[PDB]
Length: 52
Length: 52
Ligand SMILES: [Zn+2]
Ligand SMILES: [Zn+2]
Image (cartoon, rainbow over all chains, first blue to last red; front, side, top):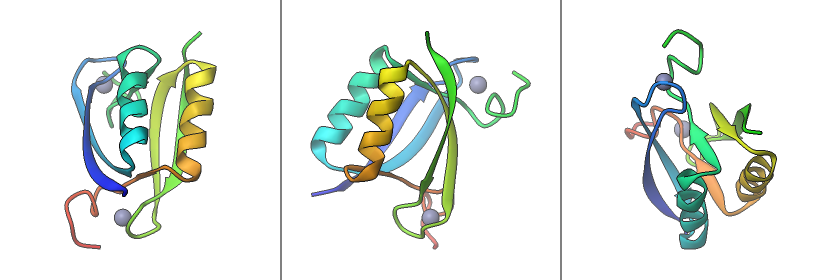
């Protein structure tokens, strides 16, 4: 069962919160949240272009 | 070494392309791309709110 899930994480560069939605099984969401702890950061729309 | 990486994937709901940037080590990016094959989909801004 894939389910919709709201990901919330601080931008790599500016620590603004970045919100994105994914559709994923339980284990993928658990995996993603584990990645977000240390190994992966998401980037906000402005920093994704460069200027904060 | 974390590096910036442009993720491109089709929206779960509408198959519009969704682009996001992450900062991640090699193995995390490999892991993410593996997830995107089957177990995880990202969702575009409009579908993230509901109306396509
Ligand atoms: Zn930012
Ligand atoms: Zn969409």
